[PDB]
Length: 142
Length: 142
Image 1 (tube, chains in turn blue, orange):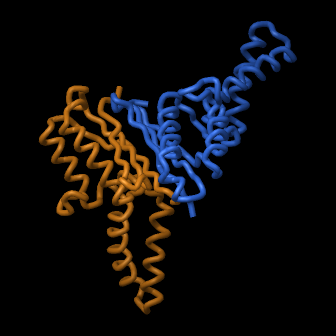
Image 2: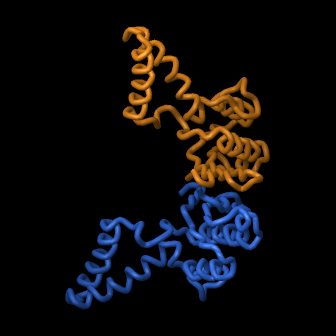
Image 3: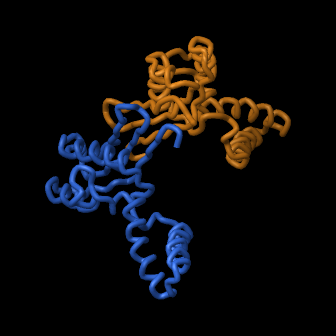
């Protein structure tokens, strides 16, 4: 069975809302405010940063390749030979992962830390494995 | 463009959370507490009642038929001839719609009103078309 909480964040303008399931090992940690603040902060980060996936593995190979091809064609359209265009696309893909993947995004409260490192920091402090299971972000009109 | 708000409800035990996009015609109504209370109440209803769809049209024909066949086979397994089993299944399907469809569920704050009628009541009072666009319900461990 899963332990943890459903963290959330509702923007003051009530135009953006997020729910996030943050899992841990025990109800004791789940009830703890340190863990509760982490779920709350993750929910706020998601609302502000709009990631589409929790992790890189969730991106469809077709979605990834299409984006990569856009990068490639653009460079090719710049007169860049295939080999260069591929390296350029390589870099833009890394950026693309930071645009859409939660764990790869710099944390809203400290952009010097990626969300995945924030999580490792929490596991080290708290002492239990912590996992962001899923999240849902609704934005008015989008 | 869409007007309205993202309503929400987080259970006190933080084990269930819901976001609901409630749409209206103007920002003036969207900012209004009557509309805001309706979005809030819909979000609470969803959290407590666990509907899977907003409306009946969203149910997969395969999901519906499978459920209907369970009803039918059960009655057939009771020695009920096909014609009777079909009428029994007909009734259980109506109930099935009330189990999983939001608009067909009796409102948590007044079970004498289906959520769809609550909405018609709000449109009559408020004076603008109101639509539940979508909702997301997260439950810890489920």
